[PDB]
Image: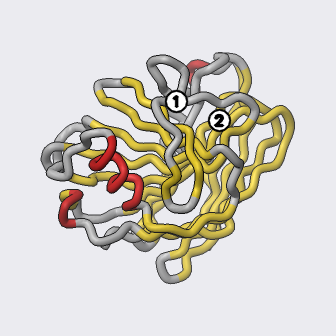
Amino acid sequence: SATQFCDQWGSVTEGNYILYNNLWGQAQATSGSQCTTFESLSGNTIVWNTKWSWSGGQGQVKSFANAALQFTPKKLSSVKSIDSTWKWNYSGSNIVADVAYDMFLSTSPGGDHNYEIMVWLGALGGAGPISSTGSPIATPTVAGIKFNLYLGPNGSMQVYSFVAQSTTNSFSGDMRDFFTYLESNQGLSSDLYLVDVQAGTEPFSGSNAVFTVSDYSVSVA
């Protein structure tokens, strides 16, 4: 049943997901808060939302409330598919935020993250990715959608970010296409392990925002 939590590290586990509030970037805000709500789970499909207002810390992410799939890590070369379906909606005033998959690679199943791959379905109000130059390295079409592709370091990782050219609130596709692409056109090794697949939103600022995920699923086959 419905479970709503507002604390910085609030979470709940449902089927194969852990849903996180994950306010890691609170301290870069002058003002604001955020609560996340699990609604329901149906087969491998989760329905949830989060609500927030944030201000200050221009250009800093305040949080990344997301649903994370719980699975056993797999080398990319042994992955047949990562089918996902996602429908979302945003409302509220002066929104600066992204809506994104965040998928992480490592050299061993328990190892640190050396790569990060993001897939932005949504770039609202100026939200910008990690990038060394600020400009695309490429503009590939993957899983039927045209992307601007960015690359840059953050933490102790390299981050590739696929940012859709049109805001895209409905999506169904094989997330493996993004890896096929990188292995093929950017030298990414397929010997690496997929170790985290997370989907949510990263807000920078706004008031009375409501991010509504009316269905989300993913599976690693």
Which quadrant of the structure image shows residue 3? bottom right
Please say if 7 is above or below 37: above
Q: Residue at x 54, y 30 (%)?
A: 129
Q: Is residue 22 left or right of residue 29?
A: left
Q: Nearer the viewer, residue 25 or 115?
A: 115
Residue 38 appears in which quarter of the rendering? bottom right
Instruction: State whether residue 212 appears in this view.
Output: yes
Using a 10 Å C-alpha cutoff, classify the residue at mark 2 as few (fewer than 14 neighbours), some (14 to 19) or many (20 or more): many
Vertical placement of residue 152 versus 84, above or below: above
Residue name at image x 47 percent, y 38 percent: 161
Disc 1: which residue: 136
Frontmost residue, 168 versus 215: 168
Question: Hey, which residue is sitting farthest bottom in the picture?
Answer: 43
2 up-or-down from 196: above or below: below
Secondary structure beneath dot 2 equals strand
**Dot 1, how many residues are within 10 Å of its Cα: few (below 14), some (14-19), or many (20+)?**
some
Q: Amino acid at mark 2?
A: Pro
Residue under label 2, please give it: 203
The mark lying in front, picked from 2 and 1, is 1
Q: Nearer the viewer, residue 97 or 64?
A: 97
Q: Amino acid at mark 1?
A: Pro
Give the CA separation, mark 2 to mark 1. 22 Å
Report the residue at 70% width, 48% height from top. 166
Q: Are marks 2 and 1 in contact (CB under 8 Å)?
A: no
Dot 1 lies on which element?
loop
* Mark 2 or mark 1, earlier in chain: 1
Measured from the top left, where is residue 60 in percent x and y? 58, 22
Percent across and percent down for residue 219 are 39, 70
